[PDB]
Length: 266
DNA sequence: GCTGATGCGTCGACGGATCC
DNA sequence: GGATCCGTCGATCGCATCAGC
Figure 1: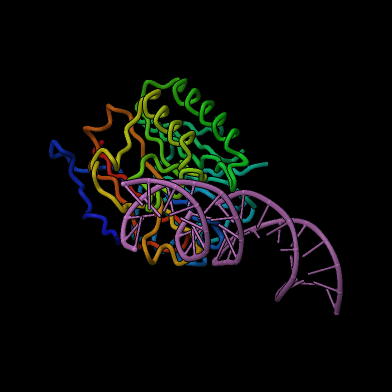
Figure 2: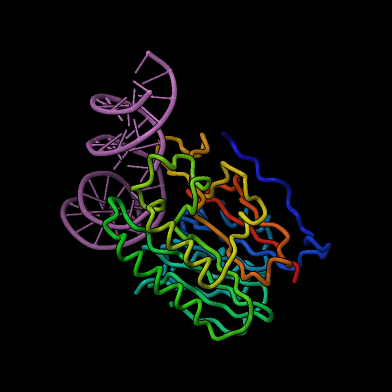
């Protein structure tokens, strides 16, 4: 079935207006994404903070369009020492920025919350890297738990797992596939329990099917909405009263993932 | 400098078997 | 004998390096 994301809810459950708009996007090659007008879409979305995954670009090769973003002028980039890579771009300067826990994680502390963006390792075709993914999950959980700040956490990005059967179109046939193994699903559950965190989208839309953020380029999967929900905003419990909406920007092209957008009343 | 071949990381369609 | 379950296989894209001119 096709999916139509509901309209943006910009007011919190207690009636407060959103003050902060965060967008996350696995861009499948930043340079290619820019050529496919991805930055035009970012400008229309006008987030306060933009998190990017799979940049496949070292800082010295960032296209010139990226220094024409006056509303996203504080930019931090991390790559493995033309694969992987993540970026964080922000209207206001963060207080602190750090990298790692490999070019997969950026941590940025703001006035009232800590933002982590991640590009979680893929278990691989034939699960050849599943054990590494499980060891990585465990190290990542411990890292997030051990964050020194008492500030609440927003974790966003491509977490490379569809948590539950409702998070992908073909759950039965994919239970031995990267992104839907019982091992990866379990690690996501432990992340939520251990940190702790809530899945913003699922909190608001607990029974909504066919809501995905990734479609394989093969077999015209996106045209059929045969997809997976791999990209998330996970929030500390204390931020739920501030949660206004968690969006899936299904129509935004340029990658095999679509953007996701969070509105918080802070 | 530029193109194209190749390598690497990144599952839905399909055929067959089992169940009642 | 329709529904379901399971294992197999070809395949999109972006970026790298390499060979050639």
